[PDB]
Amino acid sequence: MLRRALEEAIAQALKEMGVPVRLKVARAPKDKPGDYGVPLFALAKELRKPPQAIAQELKDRLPLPEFVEEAVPVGGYLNFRLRTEALLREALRPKAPFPRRPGVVLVEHTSVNPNKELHVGHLRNIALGDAIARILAYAGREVLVLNYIDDTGRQAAETLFALRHYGLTWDGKEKYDHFAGRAYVRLHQDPEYERLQPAIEEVLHALERGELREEVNRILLAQMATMHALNARYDLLVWESDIVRAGLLQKALALLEQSPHVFRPREGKYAGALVMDASPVIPGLEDPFFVLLRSNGTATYYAKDIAFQFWKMGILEGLRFRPYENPYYPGLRTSAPEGEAYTPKAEETINVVDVRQSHPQALVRAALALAGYPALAEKAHHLAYETVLLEGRQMSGAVSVDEVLEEATRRARAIVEEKNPDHPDKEEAARMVALGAIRFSMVKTEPKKQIDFRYQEALSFEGDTGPYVQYAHARAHSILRKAGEWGAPDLSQATPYERALALDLLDFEEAVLEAAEERTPHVLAQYLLDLAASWNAYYNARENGQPATPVLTAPEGLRELRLSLVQSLQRTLATGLDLLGIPAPEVM
């Protein structure tokens, strides 16, 4: 790479001076001394010395990489001006996935109750999870995506009960999970809903015995059509009923009771209950006692989360897998009564979860440590996200994802009819634009921030949207289409326009790696907006009454240079878009 190669050379140089710390390089101020710079303020106080002195010091013991023209200590920072030729050369170089590093990173996302159609709240979950999974894989990690199916849940029991109680029969045409959702909705609007609890408990009991799996599977298959349309990928399916058969709960409980911090208080407000004292691993807690088993003997959700986490990291075994029959994913495997025994042996796990319906990371963290796995305790991550509104409306009093998809595809279709009335396949074009608008919207905003999805705004080819980035890709690609083949670029003919654009291209890999390391897809999304903006300003530039950056009319040497730069940009946008699950239309 370039930026990382620079940080590596700086780190190595910092060790030869004493301080074994690693500093991050970042784009230097707008039109200032250099292209990249490193701050020396964190060390300025950690060493009680003038920042400007540390910068000059670093400059003195830093062997310049061949691509660096000059290093300049600038008030606290040490800036680097790159050699234009090397800069261009690195910008033109093809960018591909990084070297593979062994060690499974298990990403769990989606995992919705299999009792009705998906809703907007589930959109962000899927988009965020799929994106981080794709980004991590590209960054070199061995990734596996798991979808947890709670087939024994009360929510599934309620819909199955409703379908029978109301004597509803599938018409054979309505999307099955929508049919189930209607039944669920009628049940909850029923005046005698409370009086029906005993009858619902009876179905719950049969459901818990694993006797209604096929009925649940019918709903899941229809939900999966939505997952597929959202361009999400899955490797494994794990069913709650299989988790029960595997005895993960009891095994986890038996392993935990070996700990001196896992015991049953003989008296107090926990008497008879099995509790885990997390204080020895988690300081500062009013009550460091997580209940695993209530006094009545009933297992807690915390105990079950621990059991499952243990299996994910190979601490426990019991789950068996086989091919999952479905029309969307040929390689998808599901847990089942019969199959090959398997554990992902994950080095790291990532759970994509709603900020509200979430459990404290402290739980599994402490459980992993107390069980004697302090290292793995630091590798159990959570990716919590905020609520998603539809047209400024909260969906908790609702619109299905399938409807948002159809309505967005509807509007996209109209947009493709006017901007390109002669487009060969307009439907495929509309699908890509709608999907891009949705996938990009769901991930461009920091997870901690709330999102308000508005159709027109999200679909606009002019705003900070997926279609905007897609259009920049199609524009760049159309130029290459018209150019045909071209020869060797003449780097010496580069103007400040080529340099500025090439430099933005040098930030792509860092955006990908930071997003992967921090588990923040929005960083990649934001980079793509910036790159698309840079490409547009570059394309639109004019001076003295004429285009200032023409490609096809540029003289020999310059034409080739611009074509290679245009190619690098189109490839970077196509690759970036793909990591966010967004297709890259060639014609728009």
Image: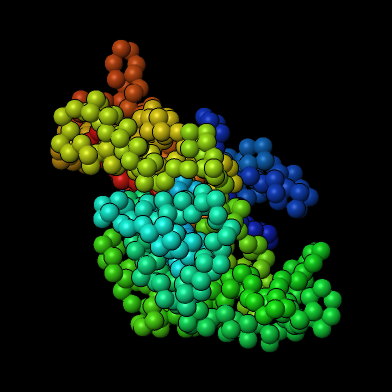
Quarter location, residue 220: bottom left
Q: Is residue 499 left or right of residue 152?
A: left
Residue at x-position 53% and y-position 30%: 30
Q: Position of residue 444 (x, y in %)?
A: 48, 42
For the question of whether residue 376 can be seen, the reply is no
Residue 553, compared with residue 185, is above or below; it is above
Q: Position of residue 298 (x, y in %)?
A: 64, 77
Q: Residue furthest top?
A: 545
**Residue toward you, 318 or 270:** 270
Quarter location, residue 257: bottom right
For the question of whether residue 262 can be seen, the reply is yes
Q: Position of residue 552 (x, y in %)?
A: 20, 28
Residue at x-position 57% and y-position 85%: 251
Quarter location, residue 358: bottom right
Q: Residue furthest right?
A: 268
Residue at x-position 33% and y-position 68%: 332
**Residue toward you, 140 or 353:** 353
User: How many numbered badges does the structure rendering display?
Assistant: 0
Q: Position of residue 476 (x, y in %)?
A: 27, 35
Q: How is the image coloured?
A: rainbow
- Quadrant of the frame with the C terminus: top left
Q: Is residue 413 left or right of residue 238?
A: left
Residue at x-position 31% and y-position 45%: 583
